[PDB]
Image 1 (cartoon, one colour):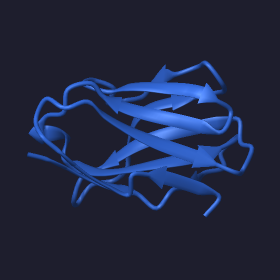
Image 2 (cartoon, rainbow, N blue to C red):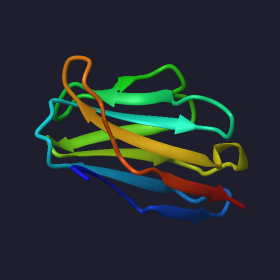
Image 3 (cartoon, helix red, strand yellow):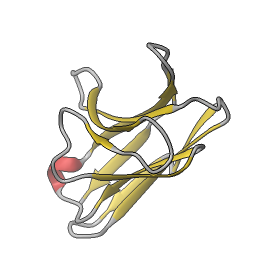
Image 4 (cartoon, rainbow, N blue to C red):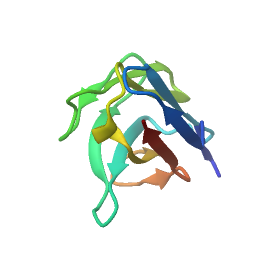
Length: 109
């Protein structure tokens, strides 16, 4: 567990801002946030090549991200919606290497 997600669970009410934090001890240059719906693969939401950089993934709409330090990468749902209920996984990495977090179950009510 060189990559830690917090919270591990989140129950949100529609409209609440939700911030998911990803913290690493890998010292990896890159960090990543994915969503995994039941029955599907990990879909890339946003990523980062280093502090202060965020890059839109394949499914960025209705998420922001922040890389405030080399070690931390946050995913922000500005205004939670039911369609955002899912399991979110972060990863650190460099080159093609990926080191995933344990996941965050998110239920939006």
